[PDB]
């Protein structure tokens, strides 16, 4: 069983979500207990499964939350919280923070078995028209508040035609008193 010459397939490298639930989230309420969370269906974030690469080597998926009003993705303000509890997931994720810039790095298997579902995190809304090391107190907020989950994996290699896909999608538009 190998790949000597079996011309009967049509699925190149591609990391598409297995399930995409509603795309909304009421991120504006959480001051009762101490730090509750907010997560809609499928723990807010949808499911993720990389399929399209039969390489026998583990790659690092580039997953993080960035804002986007047109296309130039940007680093969210404090949207980097995402602790998992209750259910136990064998997903091996990581958190990298370099000054107001957190990201997620999860090494997945391209040709073996590494399906994972992200539904155990939360967002932190504390805008105040002046994010600074002191405290954000004003009322609710007076600035856009959209978000965009970027799902793209890029492997380092010579032939650009190797493994590189982008999947930035997330219709989360905010508004006044919303």
Image (cartoon, grey):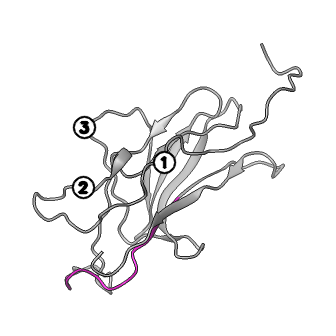
The picture places residue 174, in percent across and down from the top left corner, at 38, 74
Estimate the x, y position of residue 97 in percent, counting from the top left.
42, 61
* Label 3 vs label 1, nearer the camera: 1
- The circle drawn on residue 20 is 1
Q: Is residue 56 left or right of residue 28?
A: right
Q: Is residue 130 above or below residue 52?
A: below
* Circles 3 and 1 in contact, beta carbons < 8 Å: no
Report the front residue among 14 and 155.
14
Residue 146 has which mark?
none
161 in the magenta segment: no
Where does the magenta region start and end? Answer: 137-149
First-in-chain label (2 vs 3): 2
* Sequence-wise first label, 1 or 2: 1
Query: Image quadrant of residue 99?
Result: bottom left
Which of 33/75 is in front?
33
Location of residue 172 (image quadrant):
bottom left
Q: Could you say which is closer to the camera, residue 19 or residue 72?
A: 19
* Secondary structure of residue under mark 2: loop
Q: Are marks 2 and 3 in contact (CB under 8 Å)?
A: no
Disc 2 and disc 3: Cα gap in Å?
A: 13 Å
Q: Which mark is residue 86?
A: 3
> Which residue is the site of mark 2?
37
Q: Judge whether 36 appears above or below 137 on screen.
A: above
């Amino acid at each position: 069983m190998k790949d000597w010459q079996l011309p009967s397939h049509s699925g190149p490298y591609e990391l598409r979500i297995e399930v995409q639930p509603k795309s909304h989230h009421r991120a504006h309420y959480e001051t009762e207990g101490s730090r509750g969370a907010v997560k809609a269906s499928a723990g807010g974030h949808p499911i993720v499964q990389l399929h399209g690469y039969l390489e026998n080597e583990p790659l690092m998926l580039q997953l993080f939350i960035g804002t986007a009003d047109d296309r130039l993705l940007r680093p969210h303000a404090f949207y980097q919280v995402h602790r998992i509890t209750g259910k136990t997931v064998s997903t091996t994720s990581h958190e990298a923070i370099l000054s107001n810039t957190k990201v997620l790095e999860i090494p997945l298997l391209p040709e073996n078995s590494m399906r994972a579902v992200i539904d155990c995190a939360g967002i932190l809304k504390l805008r105040n028209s002046d994010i600074e090391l002191r405290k954000g107190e004003t009322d609710i907020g007076r600035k856009n508040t959209r978000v965009r989950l970027v799902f793209r994996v890029h492997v380092p290699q010579p032939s650009g035609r190797t493994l590189s896909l982008q999947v930035a999608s997330n219709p989360i538009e905010c508004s006044q008193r919303s």
